[PDB]
Image: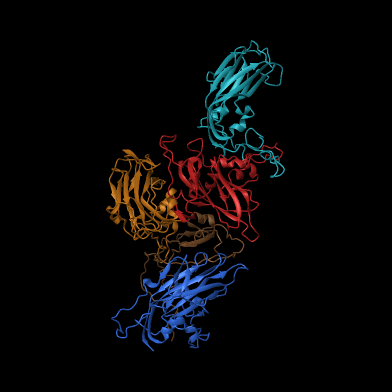
Chain colours: A brown, B red, C blue, D orange, E cyan
Amino acid sequence: FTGSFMATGKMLIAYTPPGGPLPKDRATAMLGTHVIWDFGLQSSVTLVIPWISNTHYRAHARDGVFDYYTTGLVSIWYQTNYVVPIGAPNTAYIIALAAAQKNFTMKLCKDASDILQTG
Amino acid sequence: VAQLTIGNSTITTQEAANIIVGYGEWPSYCSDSDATAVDKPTRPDVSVNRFYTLDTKLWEKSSKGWYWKFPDVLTETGVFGQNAQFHYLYRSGFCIHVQCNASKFHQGALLVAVLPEYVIGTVAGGTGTEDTHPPYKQTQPGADGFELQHPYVLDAGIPISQLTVCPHQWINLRTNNCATIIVPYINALPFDSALNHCNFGLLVVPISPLDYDQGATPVIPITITLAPMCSEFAGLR
Amino acid sequence: VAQLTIGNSTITTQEAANIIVGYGEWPSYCSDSDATAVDKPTRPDVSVNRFYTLDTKLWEKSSKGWYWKFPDVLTETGVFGQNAQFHYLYRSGFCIHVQCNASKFHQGALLVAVLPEYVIGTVAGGTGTEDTHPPYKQTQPGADGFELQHPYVLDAGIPISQLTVCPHQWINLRTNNCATIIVPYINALPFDSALNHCNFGLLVVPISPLDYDQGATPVIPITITLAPMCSEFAGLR
Amino acid sequence: VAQLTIGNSTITTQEAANIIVGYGEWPSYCSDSDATAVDKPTRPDVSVNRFYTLDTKLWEKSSKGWYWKFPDVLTETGVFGQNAQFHYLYRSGFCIHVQCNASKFHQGALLVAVLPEYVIGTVAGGTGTEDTHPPYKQTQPGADGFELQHPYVLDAGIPISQLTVCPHQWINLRTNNCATIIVPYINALPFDSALNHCNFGLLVVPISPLDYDQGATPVIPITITLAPMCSEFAGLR
Amino acid sequence: HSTAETTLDSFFSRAGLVGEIDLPLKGTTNPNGYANWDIDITGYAQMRRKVELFTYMRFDAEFTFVACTPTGEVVPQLLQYMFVPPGAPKPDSRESLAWQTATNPSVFVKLSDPPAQVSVPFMSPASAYQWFYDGYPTKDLEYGAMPNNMMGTFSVRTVGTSKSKYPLVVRIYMRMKHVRAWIPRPMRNQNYLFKANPNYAGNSIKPTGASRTAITTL
């Protein structure tokens, strides 16, 4: 959270495993694996995605692509509203930072790119 | 500050403010030599017992106060509302947590207490001659709760000025924002109905009105998060 | 809070926030069995190694970002710029300190990272057919630094979104204001030219824009103070 | 003779006929060092694992044979069908029990075997030129099961005369009436989908036709009772 | 230095008047020379509010019967007091066979004989009488109805096949003994409207106590 120091509130961050459709509302997402984030207390929070596996093969058009399907989903809802005292901006931004755990792995070197050395 | 977790639920809360263990007792289970020692009552631990975070209510200058009923509030909600409904008997303790998020430029004081057998009494027509019984939307508001209309007498002909006689805790904006309360199972019987009887009701009223200068957020979100303790059920249907 | 001193330089700084020792290595010296063991390279300790406090840059809502080159920034400045110029070779480590001064009513986030061999790439005409090479004012801005014109690609065709892969540290106004970084000598050679090659470049960009309500100071001073570590020179001229 | 119980389910069965532990392995669980060691897979013990007694099928002289798919059969049924559906992954072993009730004046022989990855193949138009794919009612019949139409080739182009190569057991009316089979989790992966993939299919076919003199009950009830062993689930939805 | 008087038992002792039966000769009131009184401890006005201080309670009651003619006169007439436990059928007439059902304790006494007096136990099938019930029994008119709080009925009548020769008046006093209470609660500050629910007058909502002019004047 990069907002003013004076701001406070709560955000609900929920993860819907692969298959589970984006939760209808906050409350239904509230029943799933979620985290209430009070940026009034902690300016940072880290969520862990238990698992993602690009292993299920797909031969659509005529071009075979080893695709996901494991599109796990991460939703974020305003648990409470944004609260601020006079003098502080009524908007703030947030930054997402990602990385993989130490249990990450990759297989099958496949050079592919849109950017190449021009003539 | 630190965050505690119970399964798939993770709430960000302050270290450990003063908790109020109602009547000095801890929500415990019920031994084998009881009324139903045959139908061994299954006690949920897995998902059933975790952090539910109810639809935040917005504090306003004009707010009169709010109240929820138990176990009603949850019999609708998730896998706990699952057990409460398709089961014959129920006994359960509760950890209730209430928090506001306000700038050091807001002022207010919410009394937050729990009241066993909270029996609502309507106005009775006005002049006192109509024997009108409170509706079902007023007797068991669910997880949205319900607003008092006569806070001073707690919509039931009792001074609120004396509500402190119940497990209560204060939330004065200029000192704290989170209040916590542990509630044991309280009833004239070991077990009872989860859909017909509301052992108690959570009360939260503005004793000192919300206030602020023009420009500061006009509504203070109050977030109720609660978790079932040593909850038991018997006789599946 | 406390103040540290290195000679005639005395800076008032916070106790000891988290420092970032780039690549896990500490700016050390270079042993006797090297390339030039004859021309014993003299290592400055006295005045040469102390606290330089560069002309503070003013953060604005529209600010795109800034960057300085090393050792260029100092080859102009004082008795260190003295050695860098009238000497043939140079190797030196760096302690960089960046701080802002803002009320708890400002908001922003500056990523501050160091990037070895930071090679600037201009626009190339616009349509992509002009082989225009970045000027000298853009390649070695001095102690005033220079402003990015395409932060997103760091004026060089690389996502900034991935700059974190370099020794970096964040400065989120609502949590900290000072960021510190220790940089070791990094180059494909033991020693090198202090005026021709810029081993690296200090980068500081607003990832979350500066913001505030009308009435609060509109510009947040960013003060860069830096000090040379285990700096060495060889071959006087 | 004696009766065994698993929760609220109590079946009256014979002492302990010969059981067939398919492939010599016992339906066990899956250790911590697997693919998903993070999302600790919850293993049902309570109600989820007990005796389900499917809608008894009636044996007739003309009966061709029956087959059910797994875990399909249960994904519809009760609290197990509860988990299978609102969960991402599944692995489970099975105890299957099949019994007939017939007078010593009926005759017949049912081969009862389990076949991994039982892939149905329809007729293909008749003449062999239509690429018709078996419906969904034929691929996953549920708890009612489905009748073979070409038993000899097991509706899939394979001799039944060779089905004995699979975990099988015989039920010759003039000797036994109940057959039991233990099935371990069999698949090319630790876990998998409970609604998309049917690890196996239970097969029960009359090899020697049912027969009796006029006057004896004309249909022999076949009762399939089955229970999940070391069943696990992961990723709730 | 002693605080014996502030105990529960001390607070609730005393036999108060909770009932009064009228058995006139000529009258609209109890024309069959008999009457049925379902035990109501609210009979003593002051009572309701005192007990409604607690959520749950438990106790035994000592009943004392005072009978005379309207002028408080004593006469040679015999009387039957019958206690019909809850679940037992009350007499519909002056000749109902209930009067003779052994399972309905009855006590006889002459008006001349001093007051009749008996103790009645904690009936309730529940662990305690509970003044408040937030639910219904398996918008409704069954709200706040904890029936398992019934103590029983008291049936009174002149002995004999024929009406009594005198107009009679029975008074029932009740001392509560061996009291235990749980979960205390706000003292009723509004007027009671019904014997069943806590409903109040939503127009006539009065401040708990005496008001004054300014908060700076006494």
The picture places residue C124, in percent across and down from the top left corner, at 50, 85
Q: Name the residue at the top extreme.
A: E76
**Residue C135 in the image: above or below residue D18:** below
Q: In this orientation, which residue lies closer to the viewer: A95 or B61?
A: B61
Of residues D233 and E20, the one drawn nearer to the viewer in this rendering: E20
Q: Percent position (x, y) of residue C233? A: 37, 83
Q: In the figure, C96 relative to D45: above or below?
A: below
Residue B15 position within the rendered picture, expressed as x and y whole percent measured from the top left: 47, 53
* Whether residue D109 is visible: no
Marks counted in the figure total: 0
Quarter of the C terminus of chain C within the rendering? bottom left
In the image: residue A88, left or right of residue C172 = right
Q: Where E22 falls versus C65 (above or below)?
A: above
Relative horizontal placement of residue C217, taking residue E125 as reference (left or right) = right
- Residue A54 visible in the displayed image: yes
Nearer-the-camera pick, B216 or E213: E213
Residue D115 vertical position relative to residue D8 in the rendered view, above or below: below
Horizontal relation, residue D11 to residue B167: left or right: left
Q: Is residue E20 left or right of residue A67?
A: right
Which is more toward the observer, D35 or D144? Answer: D35
- Residue furthest to the front in view is C8
Residue E2: x %, y % from top left: 53, 29
